[PDB]
Amino acid sequence: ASMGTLAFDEYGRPFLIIKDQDRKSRLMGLEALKSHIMAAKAVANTMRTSLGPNGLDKMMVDKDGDVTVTNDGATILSMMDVDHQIAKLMVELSKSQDDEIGDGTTGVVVLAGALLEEAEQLLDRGIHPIRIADGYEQAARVAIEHLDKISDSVLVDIKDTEPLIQTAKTTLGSKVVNSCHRQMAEIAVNAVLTVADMERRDVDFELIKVEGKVGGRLEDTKLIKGVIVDKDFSHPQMPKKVEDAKIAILTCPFEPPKPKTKHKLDVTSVEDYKALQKYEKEKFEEMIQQIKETGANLAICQWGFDDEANHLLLQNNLPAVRWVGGPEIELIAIATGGRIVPRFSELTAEKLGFAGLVQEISFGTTKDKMLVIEQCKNSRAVTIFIRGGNKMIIEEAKRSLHDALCVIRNLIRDNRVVYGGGAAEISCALAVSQEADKCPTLEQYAMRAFADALEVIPMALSENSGMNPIQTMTEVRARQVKEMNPALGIDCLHKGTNDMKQQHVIETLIGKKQQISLATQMVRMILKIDDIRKPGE
Amino acid sequence: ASLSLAPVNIFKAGADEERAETARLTSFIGAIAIGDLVKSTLGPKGMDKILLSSGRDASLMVTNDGATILKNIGVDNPAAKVLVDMSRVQDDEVGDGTTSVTVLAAELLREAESLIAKKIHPQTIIAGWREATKAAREALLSSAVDHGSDEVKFRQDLMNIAGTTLSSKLLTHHKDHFTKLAVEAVLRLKGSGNLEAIHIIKKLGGSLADSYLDEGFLLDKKIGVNQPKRIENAKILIANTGMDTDKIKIFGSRVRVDSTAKVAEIEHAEKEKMKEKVERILKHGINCFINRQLIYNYPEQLFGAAGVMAIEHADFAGVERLALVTGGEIASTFDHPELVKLGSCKLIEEVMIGEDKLIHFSGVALGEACTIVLRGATQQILDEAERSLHDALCVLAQTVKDSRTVYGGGCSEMLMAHAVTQLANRTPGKEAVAMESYAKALRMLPTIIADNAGYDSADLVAQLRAAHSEGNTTAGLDMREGTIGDMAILGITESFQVKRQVLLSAAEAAEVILRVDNIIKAAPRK
Amino acid sequence: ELLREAESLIAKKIHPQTIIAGWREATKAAREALLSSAVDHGSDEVKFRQDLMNIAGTTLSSKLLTHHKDHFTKLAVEAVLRLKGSGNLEAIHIIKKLGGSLADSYL
Amino acid sequence: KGAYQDRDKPAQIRFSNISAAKAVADAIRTSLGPKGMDKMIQDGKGDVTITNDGATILKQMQVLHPAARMLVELSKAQDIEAGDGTTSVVIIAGSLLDSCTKLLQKGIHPTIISESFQKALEKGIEILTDMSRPVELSDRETLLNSATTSLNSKVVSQYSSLLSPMSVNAVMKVIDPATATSVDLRDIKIVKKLGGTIDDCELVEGLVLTQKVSNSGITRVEKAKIGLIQFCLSAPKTDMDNQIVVSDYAQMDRVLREERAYILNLVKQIKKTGCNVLLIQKSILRDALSDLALHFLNKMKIMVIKDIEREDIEFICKTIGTKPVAHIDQFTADMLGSAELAEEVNLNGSGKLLKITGCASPGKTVTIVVRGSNKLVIEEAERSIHDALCVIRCLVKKRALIAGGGAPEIELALRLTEYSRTLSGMESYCVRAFADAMEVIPSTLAENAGLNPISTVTELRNRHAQGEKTAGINVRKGGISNILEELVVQPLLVSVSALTLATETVRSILKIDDVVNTR
Amino acid sequence: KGAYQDRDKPAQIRFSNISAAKAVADAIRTSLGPKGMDKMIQDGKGDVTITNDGATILKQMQVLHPAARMLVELSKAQDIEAGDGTTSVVIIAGSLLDSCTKLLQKGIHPTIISESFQKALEKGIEILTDMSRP
Amino acid sequence: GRVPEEDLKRTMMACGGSIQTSVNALSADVLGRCQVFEETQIGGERYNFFTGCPKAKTCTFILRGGAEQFMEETERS
Ligand SMILES: Nc1ncnc2c1ncn2[C@@H]1O[C@H](COP(=O)(O)OP(=O)(O)O)[C@@H](O)[C@H]1O
Ligand SMILES: Nc1ncnc2c1ncn2[C@@H]1O[C@H](COP(=O)(O)OP(=O)(O)O)[C@@H](O)[C@H]1O
Ligand SMILES: Nc1ncnc2c1ncn2[C@@H]1O[C@H](COP(=O)(O)OP(=O)(O)O)[C@@H](O)[C@H]1O
Ligand SMILES: Nc1ncnc2c1ncn2[C@@H]1O[C@H](COP(=O)(O)OP(=O)(O)O)[C@@H](O)[C@H]1O
Ligand SMILES: [Mg+2]
Ligand SMILES: [Mg+2]
Ligand SMILES: [Mg+2]
Ligand SMILES: [Mg+2]
Ligand SMILES: [Mg+2]
């Protein structure tokens, strides 16, 4: 574009102000604003086709050629190798929506792009970009209040989980896993409700292990109330099933003790050598005897062990797992109700965990084995074991189920619920239009633009569903204003009715509010930029 | 406007973003390329490919396995990579169907491109395909038959399934031979699914019919120097001890003395420790000692002086298979002999195969593991025979697990297509036009099977479709003469597991490739 | 489209001489059907003029002149009737003058 | 009108494979038979190789076409199963494929060609078995004749008079002739030593070692008691980390003295058994023979050979009845081997050899010392002697003998022509192709001998039709004759395995229809 | 569900043309009116030209986009027929296309836009004639 | 563990204790105190909150926003 400085002097002497000013570029003012708006519109029009049940996916290829098929706006924009700084800002915006909510990552981008596209026409008419940003802030406040007004509430109890299942089904309608729609919603709900702190209103996702294994069918995905590990029993002649398992969780390798300090044990005689030999033997025997006397029928170590320990476990009928990772050790403890023991001397019958079933699982013609721990009493940990025909659908299933879990988390944090299908956006657009009518200052135009931008989500849903955008949206808006019903939206699935409260299409109020707030704040930060400086090449 | 065709390009130098039609074009072309590649290997009259790597090793493989073919090609189309991974996952789940799932996915995607050209949304298409998948699932499951109860009929079904799995492969030359081999080898597992128990030894030379299934077991390990070579009524100790400069696990331990005499005393004490270990071993009352780890010169000498055949450096798989074949317990501690179970076999000798000697265990106790000696004229023949045997053994194991069987020769695909057709002509809208395409692909499967033989695929598939519409649910392709016949009589039966997996994985991959309307590539790492 | 169908048939394993044979038979059948469906009104002067106006309208429908089709149809028909049966299309000179609307065009 | 066959790449691939295979066959056709010559092969690194062995030639020339690689593997498989016929098998495969050329052109399906070839193969196995005659391993003249036949093709054929009796003695010394069903040629050790000529090759009944003697002055030992020592004669070293901490001046002298005393006690326990020859295994991580130990052994008049390899131990024990000792406590007299002589012999300034000759327990093992004027001729002498041993091995495995000089191939051509005339159909063309393909070995033998191949092969076919089924190409007279008077016989196993493996390789290559370039 | 519109290149081309035209219009928007200023244009040969004339400006800046070339031809036609308004005409064209942007996005067919624009044009000629005075 | 030095010094100034290199004299004068300690989720991250310190001579801003540079310009403001 334009250069930093183009004089070189009114006297002919060199004029060097900035380093590599000749290789550097600069864009200033309205042309800079329009470049920003063009970039943002490009990103938003890329994303808008991945919106809604009839939304399509994108195939992302990384540097090393790995393929990722997804409908998740945050994953798409993260996999996208963007160079434009405004596109980077939009990627950050979507990532922020994903961090805070875990859903809406495409709505935020579409809405921000629409806001900037309307600011484009407002700037053409000559309004100051800061005035545009302030009108957008005003309209965003109005829309947030209207969302709080039209919101509904759902019960987050563990007895009737139908509202939560409906919410999760709405969230998962747009993902490839809608083939197992209700199974996935059920397992997301049961997962969060099993592991969720109702009193604190907190949900720790480290306690939800989402594991995937190629093979089987997507319908085989299930919720394990317990843990799955990628290990097998240490000895090949151990039993592959253990019922009523009393579990000893240990972070001590079944090996002779060893000081952490630099140590040298000196052997100075045949008697010293034989004493050392007998010490080693008796250490192994004493370890196994302590584990047996604790009453355990199963051992789980974190640091692996050797041939003598393995065979002694086998002889003493103590199936054992080794080389289990720290996180899985923690999850097994939490699930079985056991305490992690750092050495055998500290092991007691009360520190043991209990699992009604510990089994080794095969996966066809593979030679790889997995260990399932389940039938615990009150497991505060849980595992989601995902199956499918390829790693692409497995990864998409993982991220979609993450979206569902995050949505249930947002419900546990705030039970208020708005109805989707663009209905909430149409209602907020109506409210913003009314407030713009009551506004007599120059921000009227910015607020009308905000309404026209809010209306892009119903239009996008209709377009992706093949309906005519303008016709469908105007008819449902007219119906909303005539018969007061903010649950009137786009019949994306062609169920006949436009009532999203009847179709059980459900969004989170904090989710929608976060969408609107993030889009408005980022659009403000973009409109406030009027000069770009970048290094050459 | 668009991400790519905008006044500003939003991408780093080297990236790209194919939009709707361009993306669907590259996806369909990649998938259909993969499918056209992997077909012509489909069916009894399918032909093999030469892989001919281009690395500095220039590996050379002659394969008929679709999974192997797809694994060994340099693919750069993302949809093609999807199909490749799908075939790999099929090969992991079951051992057969890796070419049929790929061909099915490719044909479905061809029909989907046709429908897109017919101006049908690639969500109406996926909807209709899901309905068709349901119909096909139900038709297949209703057509399945189970014979696991009847032992004789189950054995016959196993022989027929092995024969059908081998028909397509290089072993069809000696199919009646390798079928019996594979069935006996899978029955020797006694219900277990451990396919590692079935060891396959490829010995260059001899004819492919010289291959056999050892009545006992064979091991490619050596015997010690001063130790016997023949042992009758062998009592065997399978171990995982060190027996090789075996040091006390205390690692800070060091010998620090003031006298070479004391150093010599400590060395003698080490030797005495090894001797006492060997004596504890011999107190089990054994004639053979197998160790997963090495056996050094001194314990070798001790076992020789004791008259024990000491086989060393067997591996984890070696000792597992030996425990399965003899009944012993892999041990590492010898302070409780009453608790260590020993293995038994009537005889252990050394036999010759090709130019190499192998330990031969005859008269074994359990036999829950097997050894198959594969002989052949070329290393390529041997590798393809191993791959084909692996296919057959995996399928027979999966059938012993789930005894449900399903007739082959296109009977199953035609039955599913018949059900999909009923659903289609009873359903309104363009979902019917997509179900009809689903059925067209299902029919195109046996169409390709017949094409690869050289028959009038169109005429024969028309006859099959007419038969399955009339109600002859057991009509299939008779590939001897090139007509239609009764699969129940001809013995052309497949595993319901494998056919269901083919169907479902193909439909799933086609769905996941069809949902794509944009391909955003990132700058190659180069 | 014919070549697309021909690729489909080749994939169906049909010889590209059996295909040409059937295509020649089909061309004969189509020729005869077309020739039997054809109608002539050159005798009746009024109906022939109407057919000329209809043909000009159909030819212009696909083109940028469909905006002023009722105008350019009359233009083209009058200009072709001014030739008095001759087929010399060089006799019809067309002068493109930049400016004015497309409906300002005239004969 | 059947199926159009819209694709031509399968046929192109078949034709390319056939062309590559026929090219390999025609390249090595010149190294077939007694009148065939050798090829020199200079590797990329510059390793030169003169050879007449088909397997060696094909493995050494880095062929690139897949079909040629498969023919290489075929020749290796024939070398394994029979050790002789590695050129005939490749020529047969190439010829069968060259016939598949015209069959494919005629328009027969590759599957039909393969099945008809399997039929012809079974019939040919029948024919060869009918031709064969049984043999007793006691028939030393028959064994000598088999070995001479195997050697006639090789550079070592003027020395056949020397290397055939050796190649028969060696195998007959490493097997129990009454019960043996095979032989392990690792029991026969071959020692290539430059110098002299191939007429200097030797059969040593005892043991031969390239390791040098460490003692100076003690090179010859009569009435030798020999012991294998797998432990180290040097200062003690525990398997654990060991040190000797000195804190007083007296401990230094004490350390030196106790080291001397340890070593001396070791060598005295060795001498006490009567051992005068000591083979010490090779030891990394520790000195197997310290300077003190060598001094003491030499003073005690004991020959010492260290650096024995951990893979030659089983051989040395099998040879001289020794038992390997890994702890000095178990080193006694019953663990020794008695040999009537152990000498370090010099070979006319061309190196040295340790020969342990004479043995009270000479257990089924022999060694062959290969001499020669060049590295190339030595290597080819080794390969040819291996071919002779493998011929004797074939005779041991299958007690059946077949005539040579292209007689089996000609009988095959003839009887399979008859079989083809009887098997009317489209298989008839393929079987007749199989027959005319097997008619190529006699044609090649004639061409290489220098005769008119057409006339010679027609005379052979005519005489075999008359009934002289033991009639072949007499390169000594220059025409056809009863080949048993020339004593050209070979084990039936050679021809049978060659035919079988060639047919399997041809069927495999016919089942191929495409080539991919993986990555 | 109507017609899927399996192809997006038509829409991309429409949007690119509209963008190019709007860019030309916005580039020459500053040379409109009594308070508008002139542009200097240095040809590749170095021939300098200061001007406020829309036709001259557009002919002298070697526009490359097809739509921009067509706007140049439009301004030349206006210079022929009237000799005044060569900037207003280009600005009007660019603005009409900038409106076609949002219409297309709303999902109206270009043919419907064209016909409705013809209707509006006829009505606007009527309105301007009513405004006129002899 | 591995708590940053600045956050430790702020926790000290807030709760009212001292940082101890030795655990041999852990008196109530050196221990700190707050009315509430919690670990909560804040936008994808987990944060430890010490709240209720009445003698606190320190405070901690927690800034939200949709981009790294958004939050950086907020911090600069
Ligand atoms: N079954 C449905 N019917 C109508 N609208 C739906 C349905 N499911 C989801 N939507 C709407 O689609 C919009 C886009 O959500 P989606 O794209 O699936 O998630 P994200 O926006 O997080 O990627 C939401 O605003 C929601 O209201
Ligand atoms: N003897 C036979 N007669 C008829 N059809 C057969 C026969 N053997 C196999 N098939 C068919 O061929 C297919 C198997 O071909 P194969 O090369 O194994 O493909 P995949 O690798 O996908 O299993 C099956 O669909 C089966 O119906
Ligand atoms: N003295 C001989 N007279 C005639 N034919 C011979 C004689 N010696 C060998 N042959 C023939 O030569 C062939 C062996 O040639 P050789 O170079 O060893 O080929 P290959 O390596 O394939 O055995 C045998 O078929 C044998 O019949
Ligand atoms: N003194 C004036 N006061 C207000 N408007 C004026 C005046 N002079 C010209 N204009 C307006 O400016 C326009 C002419 O600008 P000009 O640079 O000639 O553009 P164009 O070449 O497109 O006509 C006319 O539309 C006219 O209404
Ligand atoms: Mg969502
Ligand atoms: Mg198969
Ligand atoms: Mg026209
Ligand atoms: Mg030979
Ligand atoms: Mg003017």
Image (cartoon, coloured by chain):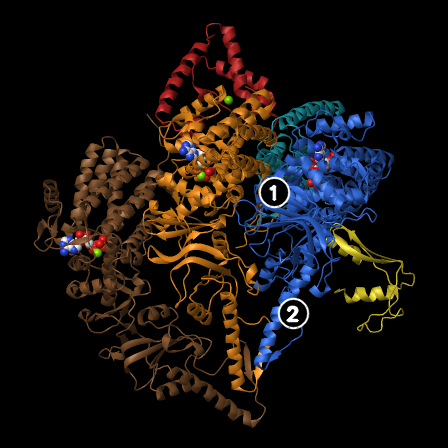
Chain colours: A blue, B orange, C red, D brown, E cyan, F yellow
Task: Answer with left or right where residue D214 lies relative to residue B273.
Answer: left
User: How busy is the neighbourhood of tag 2: few (under 14 within 10 Å), some, or many (20 plus)?
Assistant: some
Residue at mark 1: A387
| The quadrant where residue A424 appears | top right
Q: Chain of mark 2?
A: A
Assign a secondary structure to mark 2: loop
User: Picture coordinates of residue B276 (x, y %)?
Assistant: 52, 71
Horizontally, is E6 left or right of B55 in the view? right
Which residue lies under the disc numbered 2? A257
* Relative to D464, D65 lies left or right: right
In terms of depth relative to the viewer, which is nearer, D252 or A75? D252
Q: Could you say whether the residue bearing mark 1 is in a helix, strand or loop? A: strand
Q: Position of residue F6 (x, y in %)?
A: 79, 66
Instruction: Classify C5 as above or below B43.
Output: above
Farthest residue, direction right: F54
**Residue neighbourhood size for the residue with mark 1, other residues' Cα within 10 Å, grouped as few (<14), some (14–19), many (≥20):** many
Is residue A206 among the parts visible in the rendering?
A: no
* Residue type at the position of mark 1: Arg
Instruction: For residue D326, say whether it is visible.
Output: yes
> The residue under label 2 is which amino acid type?
Pro
Q: Chain of mark 1?
A: A
